[PDB]
Length: 364
Ligand SMILES: Nc1ncnc2c1ncn2[C@@H]1O[C@H](COP(=O)(O)OP(=O)(O)O)[C@@H](O)[C@H]1O
Ligand SMILES: [Ca+2]
Ligand SMILES: [Ca+2]
Image (cartoon, rainbow, N blue to C red; front, side, top):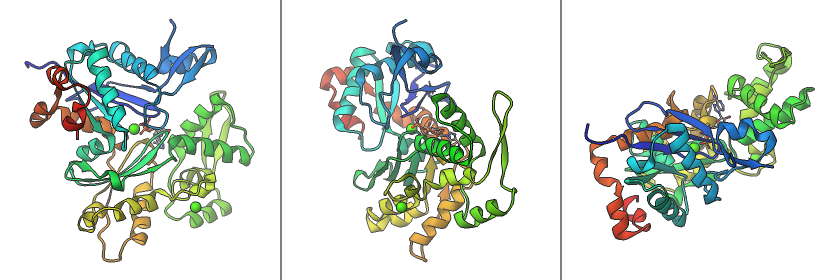
């Protein structure tokens, strides 16, 4: 091979995924955190491990970069610590959130070429990459991560900004809600350490009920839905209706005091904002992505809820890839490996010729 490996970096609100184009999975995943004492800067797992003696910062808390000084440190960490490569020696494909401000796109571009001296780079919308990973160029993606969720209609490879909806309800909120209801049950999960334990309980024992009320009735009259969970100190606790009550908040945000529409309604509203001529393509190609869409039963629940909102004559299909937790990264690996994509990279030459604003033309 003549070309060096290209890098794929998925910038997540909670976890960053990094690896090499062509691979089937990211080589590294770490917390999008930077910490400094209350070694001068700590990034990733280490910052989390030593959080006790540090003040943590979340530079991309809700999907959008808010502090470029710390984001630069996360990227430095990604190259030198996680992937152990020199960025000046490899093209880099970066991901961005839907509705990312134009100025931010230019900033990312300038930093890659001027700070890291990348030989080439490109930036793609997360939702679009997930759709690519599913083998489609048209459809609507419901991306629910750690700090944010989005419904992104995509037609012929292009996201439709006017129809994109943002929901400030995701994995983080669900974890805290589970801590709250488990505490109401009689336990006590309130500390940061306990938040990590509940996050684990959430990822392992929660599920989306097909019918909330029926599930609540079953849990109230029997122990058939109860599951045991063992804490590190040996204590075994019981999780009952909390298993499905937690993710139910995605469909009924009021449980969290939020007036926002649930994910099914948000998906429907995005589709309705699109040209009537492509709505059927979206209904027939609703793809789920992100860690928060991993709950067992979520696909069937979405199918049921969307069917209730859409015309009776509409064909509804929910696609839930088993590997959807990393579909963004995988889509990037696929894209960066495409023969026709090689001409699309922004080269250092092109950057020197046109400057940061070239990103709008090259990465439309
Ligand atoms: N199996 C699972 N069930 C439910 N939630 C999960 C599961 N696996 C991961 N999560 C949650 O998904 C979120 C992270 O997903 P991710 O798409 O990586 O987000 P981001 O890109 O914003 O960091 C976290 O809140 C995590 O707890
Ligand atoms: Ca993400
Ligand atoms: Ca409501």
